[PDB]
Amino acid sequence: SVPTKLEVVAATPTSLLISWDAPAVTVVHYVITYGETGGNSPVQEFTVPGSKSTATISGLKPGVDYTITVYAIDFYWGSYSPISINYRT
Amino acid sequence: VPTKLEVVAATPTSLLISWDAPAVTVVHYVITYGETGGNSPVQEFTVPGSKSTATISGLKPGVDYTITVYAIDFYWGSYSPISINYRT
Amino acid sequence: QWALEDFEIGRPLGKGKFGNVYLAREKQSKFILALKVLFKAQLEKAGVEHQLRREVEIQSHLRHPNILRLYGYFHDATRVYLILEYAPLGTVYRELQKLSKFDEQRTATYITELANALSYCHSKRVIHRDIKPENLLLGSAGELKIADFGWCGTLDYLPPEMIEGRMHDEKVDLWSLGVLCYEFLVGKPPFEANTYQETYKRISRVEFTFPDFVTEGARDLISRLLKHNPSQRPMLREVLEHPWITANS
Amino acid sequence: QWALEDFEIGRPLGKGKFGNVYLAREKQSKFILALKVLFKAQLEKAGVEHQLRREVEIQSHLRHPNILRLYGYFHDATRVYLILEYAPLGTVYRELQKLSKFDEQRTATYITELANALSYCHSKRVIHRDIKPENLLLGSAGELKIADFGWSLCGTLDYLPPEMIEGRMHDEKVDLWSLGVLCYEFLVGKPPFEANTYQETYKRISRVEFTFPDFVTEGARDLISRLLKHNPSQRPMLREVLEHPWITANSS
Ligand SMILES: O=C(Nc1c[nH]nc1-c1nc2cc(CN3CCOCC3)ccc2[nH]1)NC1CC1
Ligand SMILES: O=C(Nc1c[nH]nc1-c1nc2cc(CN3CCOCC3)ccc2[nH]1)NC1CC1
């Protein structure tokens, strides 16, 4: 599970701050996908520099549950095995 | 390289030398020996690179010999020899 | 997107240069396969990722019965996993270690498989495929399968236009093909010398000899394949139609 | 013959995982030199020790103003020392990483010098010279010097044509593709096919997928395009590249 420490640091009815433990390895960039869990509408993607260890997701509806999947991309060997966590807010 | 080169055993007719592993791939070793000081040109025979010992036969007793061995790298040639004196 | 939890790892098959290989079965399909596991630490210390990553893309577009299949790859924090076809009969390098050499029936057969695999690569404009005993596996039906990934050296199998530092073409495969045929019969590289300076000359001057137990048919083929001038070397189509292999296959 | 006891090793000039390069000078004459140290283990472990031994002989029987010289070599139990010419102004990589972009003349000038060497190398059958920024040094008079003496978002893939990456037949026409890539890098400040992953870049090279920013002049946009072509034969000759108007105008 790379990244490993995918968790929620801050949150709010408008936006949501996510974080993950530094991979201790060269990462080109992170791909984050989030959407209504349980098999709902398609997800939304956006990338994050490979140096950062956090990410902000804005424009969410309060109450719904979301599966936040974070992909760590390795230049040579593509993405690692992602890590997903559910969050309600 | 070789860094160490001692005489583990010997006889009045021949001698047996040994050296250490240089932590590097060696093609083979060239063994040269003769009366240390200068009586006549020395001899030269080769020993495979995997072996760490040799046997020089045909040495008279009571002759301070000077055996010199220098390894040979496959790509970069010979190493700096390491000479040691011994009295038969 | 494969993952380490998708396979039933089992008996180890060997120990490569940058890691070890295991035997496993695809959980969701029960398909057997070889799973090469290479430690990144050993890969980055020598800088060989791009050499293997480049070979992956080259062979990924190459799917021939005599070329080991690469179905996919995955990685983790400290290991890179290659999902490789299984070869129940082992590696040809093990055969030459157990037999010391091959009979003209086994060589002419292997030379016929490689000449085909090489011609298929030429069709895709791919040249200079390492076909040393290390990178040759034996499939189920005794089928020789090429496996170019990683894990003197390759110098012995280099033509005289590459050690000298000059442009080369598809004829480097005819050289290595003849060099390989010489080892299967004799069990030694024809241009194996003590030092680099010596190994270089023998290859640049073509200084090799045929033992007494080398027939005229084989001697003629090796002679034709081992030509200093790449233009003087034959064509893969002609090799397949050589009398020595048309009778020993 | 050479030995380690004939050099006054001055301050370092570079420290990496592949090797170290120290400032040095001949003792008898006090002649400034550059000593490049490499480890056999890494070379043997990677299968490059042969290539390194091949370059030493090749780069000893050829001299050129824009080609760094190899004044000899020696070795010990673990290391392999190379006696290299000194280059006061450093490598174009660092000078590029700082300024990011070069003048329209500096680029056209660098391309002019590199083209001459490649023709001098392509004549002696010495095809394919790695001329990435890391292997380009700057001399006292501000001139380039190709320094291909082993190792040193993407890596060495950004400078290879589709013939090399795909393992196909290559010839002296790969040098032209490199000039087009390097020329694009001096003006824009990044390889044209640079991407985020190895596969992404591999696809852009094999498909020749790149674009010119607006600030790229028209003259440079014609030479770089004439060099970055999939077919290696369609490319020009090192003589025609020297005759390109944009070069003859801004170069020096
Ligand atoms: O590519 C490799 N292996 C393979 C990819 N596909 N298939 C293999 C491989 N390696 C094989 C090795 C053996 C024989 N040994 C004795 C019996 O079981 C353990 C190994 C037999 C079949 C083998 N197949 N490298 C490791 C060193 C062998
Ligand atoms: O072979 C190399 N370099 C050289 C070959 N010939 N000369 C060099 C070299 N290395 C150079 C480094 C510098 C800048 N430093 C700060 C100012 O004083 C000199 C050192 C300038 C010029 C240099 N030239 N490899 C470089 C270390 C990665």
Image: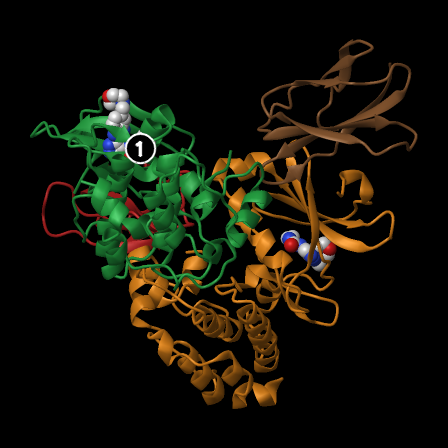
Chain colours: A brown, B red, C orange, D green
Given residues C220 and D64, the one toward you in this image is D64
Residue at left offset 64%, top offset 65%: C67
Helix, strand or loop for disc 1? helix
Viewed as shown, does residue D36 lie left or right of D227?
A: left
> Residue D179 placed where, x, y %?
34, 47
- Residue sitting at 52 percent across and 87 percent down? C242
Are there few (<14), some (14-19), or many (20+) residues within 10 Å of tag 1?
Answer: many
**Mark 1 CB in 8 Å range of ligand 2?**
no
The percent position of residue B50, horizontal first and vertical second, equals: 42, 50
- Residue D146 visible to an observer of this rendering: no
Q: In the current view of this chain or complex, which residue is farthest to the left?
A: D29
Determine whether C226 is above or below D179 in the image.
below
Residue C95 lies in what quarter of the image? bottom right
Task: Work out whether residue B24 can be spotted.
Answer: yes
Instruction: Please state the horizontal and vertical placement of residue C165, each as a whole percent of the image.
Output: 31, 59
Vertical order, C243 against D124 (above or below) = below
For the N terminus of chain C, the image quarter is: top right
Circle 1 sits on which residue?
D92
Q: Nearer the viewer, residue C98 or D12?
A: D12
Relative placement, left or right, of C174 versus C56 is: left
Chain bearing tag 1 is D
Residue D247, how many percent across, how many down?
Answer: 25, 45
Q: Is residue D243 above or below residue C216?
A: above
Disc 1 marks a residue whose amino acid type is Val
Which residue sits at x=28%, y=57%? D126
Q: Quadrant of residue C94?
A: bottom right
